[PDB]
Length: 53
Ligand SMILES: [Hg+2]
Image (tube, rainbow, N blue to C red; front, side, top):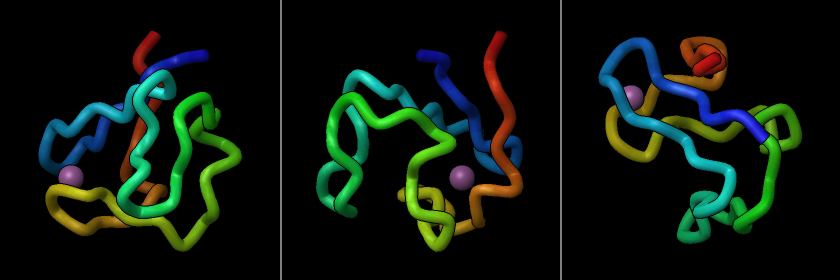
């Protein structure tokens, strides 16, 4: 599974860690994160994230 980065602030979503405090469990692919989730650091939506290749 690929990491994704917030292109506004630089936060990296790592699927191995998830974002458990906001209900995203370890092992969750970015695409499967509920679409109302926002960056835990700056609060922008999923549509500002890009795949890290
Ligand atoms: Hg951000």
